Length: 203
Length: 206
Ligand SMILES: [Cl-]
Ligand SMILES: [Cl-]
Ligand SMILES: [Cl-]
Ligand SMILES: [Mg+2]
Ligand SMILES: [Mg+2]
Image (tube, rainbow over all chains, first blue to last red; front, side, top):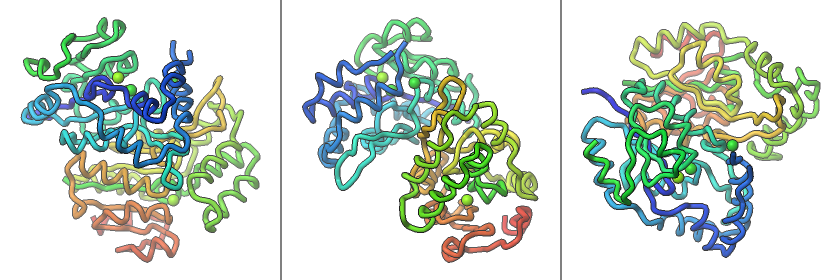
């Protein structure tokens, strides 16, 4: 019945929060992490530097913070509506799977691809590696999935909010800029300026 | 709808990605020492990988790609892929190695996918750093799980082929576990062993 692919960004798309930040202030280093943005932004260095600010953070805490992010309204509703229309629903995140694994199960996403916060003796050791370590990581994984599930660009829908989602926007027919930054809105097929994911259903 | 997953180093290609590069760059003994120890409980897979890659610093990317695209396939390679696809098998490759190589073979054998690690590049030369998907010895297993859930394919319909201990992770979630000219440790949890450097020998099992 026609197989389709839907990919969601995580931070500020599914959850009305930025994982690395909620993590930062939970450990009391938000004011430092907030300023770590190296640059035409270097996503890789910025990310690994912020993560290091988390050295020694106990895992139970990090896991608690990551599994408690607030979702945007319509989240579940949107995802169920997509699945009932033969959509494979996936989530891409420059964030971490402590977060993405939880929401993948909660929203019944078919898959989630993010990075891992390396743990040593029950605490974060400040290191990170994974699927989304570079700024063009989403576009790449999208091509991977399309070739894997054998779904075309024409049958792909993408939803994100930041500059980082551009690499994903390139290989999609439907591009939704959800409460997005100027750069992303300007390449979108549709813009949603209201904090409710259900608004996307009419699509 | 079935799933067939292949290990890369010493399973699809009769070579070990990391050392071919090490020697091609002249840091073979250093890497060799480290490859050992790792196989002999001294250091975990993760630190090994990171340490062995640092020995590749400054290596031209073009030369690195060239070496990675020159690895000798195992005889019967294309045969099996072709055979598997007829039996409605989604052919995928897992590697604790690098996509610079697995991406080439992925495209050559037209595999549906290939999941590896990445060699960071700075000013057209290897950085000495690596990051990615398969950086831990339990990585392959965890990825197989993600795959099974994504495609909605059961373990019963999963066929795995590997040669090393690192492959025990994806063995634990497979019905058909194949040890291709493997180490005894993998042979132990195996379901079929192939002690012949010929990959078409798996066809009778598919
Ligand atoms: Cl992101
Ligand atoms: Cl980057
Ligand atoms: Cl490996
Ligand atoms: Mg975002
Ligand atoms: Mg091997």
